[PDB]
Image (cartoon, rainbow, N blue to C red; front, top):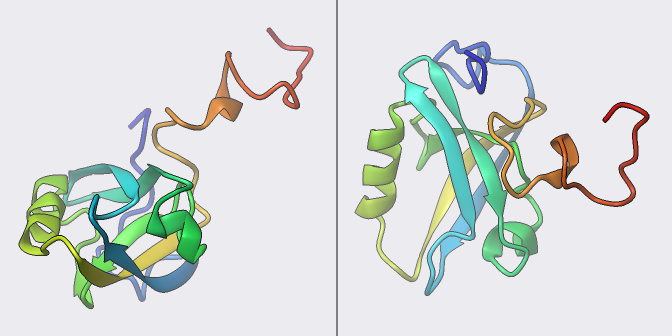
Length: 129
């Protein structure tokens, strides 16, 4: 697992990390975060990133790279990314969801995070190309 494959133990209680259970209001756009991972019932969801406009950043409790572990107290920890999307499809616009986010695990994929590689923040300077 190059872009993922963390320690998957299918139980939020057994996994390490910081765990914060925050409700994300599915607003008009729905959720202000994106996820990546959930590749398998053994690869985790993590917040690909979130819109600084959206409830995720606004709530403040959700950040880029937090591993989605659960939804509605239902362990959706790499349920399957297919299943997780289905559950969010299960949830309607204008809703909200108490989600379990584990933070501490590095971003699986880093699109909105500049900071990881080339074309990054200009406050991110390294002697390495």
